Image (tube, rainbow over all chains, first blue to last red; front, side, top):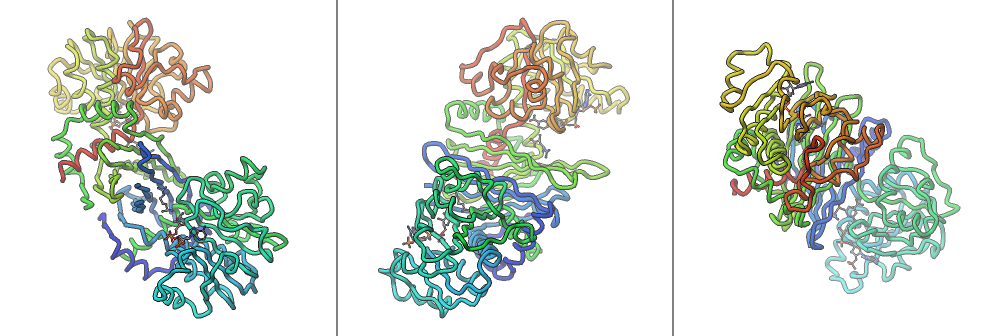
Length: 308
Length: 312
Ligand SMILES: NC(=O)C1=CN([C@@H]2O[C@H](COP(=O)(O)OP(=O)(O)OC[C@H]3O[C@@H](n4cnc5c(N)ncnc54)[C@H](OP(=O)(O)O)[C@@H]3O)[C@@H](O)[C@H]2O)C=CC1
Ligand SMILES: NC(=O)C1=CN([C@@H]2O[C@H](COP(=O)(O)OP(=O)(O)OC[C@H]3O[C@@H](n4cnc5c(N)ncnc54)[C@H](OP(=O)(O)O)[C@@H]3O)[C@@H](O)[C@H]2O)C=CC1
Ligand SMILES: NC(=[NH2+])NCCC[C@H](N)C(=O)O
Ligand SMILES: NC(=[NH2+])NCCC[C@H](N)C(=O)O
């Protein structure tokens, strides 16, 4: 010790672990007070040069705590996790976590879809076409009997047909769309996976009530839906204690639209321990993720056990 | 990269660096805005098992930032406390060094209070008192000893009454002007500067029981709301602290005073950034002068940055 895993060895070990299971237990653990999730901490660099966010989690059940540090350098973004023993207080592992973050962000949203979407939903829509979108598809594809998967990204119109093959070769049911409108037609679940700062979708412009997931974070107060729309949705989030205070749309809505965090109907720990209100679909249903360091300390712990 | 430094290499690299200078410039850097010092974060472990504190700094001027993580693990036989620092580049956002900082912490804690003493104590003070006799007090002594013409140095700690003859000599051999004492009372007599370096949870000294007004430094942090002086006595001192924006919100005495005794953080007359950039009120000695340190990550990142430059 301490072992230093870089990108290569990380991807390798990331392929050998069951992320959804790791996460499912984590949150259950979280709910039970066997895991602690401090708020994230953003620290600005001087001279507009950028920032970094640190993420914590404590996994007492595994006897490890850690920190993930993620700097935005002006447009360079990285992620590095340091895992520490809760027994001898020594470092166990330092791990490049570029890929582990993509995984856990997708898997985390997957657990929301499995718990929140109608059991017999059939239509899926996916906005954004980068790795997080990609990864989103892989972790949600087998969660319901999807009869149609549409994704759409501005770039795709003028896209290399080869790259399209890569996308189309992630699920045979998937077809590339031409608009955001088209993709989310008659959709039951709509997974916003963009880097947008601003709304990529208005919920009250949907044909029918749908589950709407959002993961956008890398922008001051970034949001993927109109902040005012939260007042006409059934709002969920990864974690109730921390995310409402940092999620762009929730901040904007409470400051301007009369929205109150107390409206959040449930979070992952509550849903996955049967202590949250499953929603009707009399109104759209929104789930917000911004990441959570438990997600990051669980993954890095997983790699460490294998490392060992 | 990233090079991993364990204890031995750390102490040796530590031995080859001017902690005081690095730190002085650091705080000047702080004051200019070329360096950022976020508050410290404390996260409790479940089931009374302990906690950890993280410390941040941004050293834009050195092109790096970092985190120092310090856990307190409660083991029945004893409490384990450690310190590890991770230093990240602000250019490529890659890790540059991961470094055991058990001793770097000791250094920086001593050197910091040193800068307060060089900035706050009379130019012609000649009496020095040291409470606590651990490595932290010992380091304070080696960083404050050449700062004035000391005519007498006294340290006291409860263990010293009945200790290894030779142990005494280890300490004695740090300064020829030093003497051990049999009480805290005895050590602080006619004291110009009194450097509390203990692990006490509660007061080891009432400043209103001193013969004359002195500079009184404090470091104790290892306890919930730990304090080395009565909280109420701050309302009758000229209070300084390492950094004004953070330390008042977490320091025990200051918390308790503001809660119970009508004290108000606005009272803090200055911090090290201000002092060392000439925008703080050096005080008179009509009242005792108090300086509070609780550690600040920028100190940790500076020192780690130093080792990394040598390592390179
Ligand atoms: N919640 C969490 O834990 C995390 C969240 N994130 C957030 O998610 C993003 C990660 O995605 P990633 O794939 O890595 O980044 P990319 O930039 O590679 O992909 C983002 C995609 O979103 C699409 N997009 C951007 N704007 C719009 C719009 N107005 N309408 C429709 N689609 C749009 C882009 O399409 P085009 O190709 O046309 O640009 C792009 O393909 C980050 O920007 C971050 O904000 C990231 C990490 C963790
Ligand atoms: N502000 C900062 O930046 C930092 C502060 N600290 C604080 O300082 C301590 C670290 O010092 P360190 O030397 O390593 O710890 P040690 O436990 O090794 O030494 C503590 C010393 O304080 C003395 N002491 C304890 N209680 C009393 C009392 N009631 N009256 C007089 N003396 C007393 C002890 O004497 P005896 O031997 O007789 O018990 C001992 O010599 C930690 O407890 C922590 O709270 C630590 C690191 C950084
Ligand atoms: N503003 C920043 N420094 N962000 C870094 C990117 C954070 C990224 N979404 C993560 O959770 O790893
Ligand atoms: N309660 C804790 N976990 N404290 C960690 C030790 C703090 C120590 N004074 C340092 O600066 O390293």
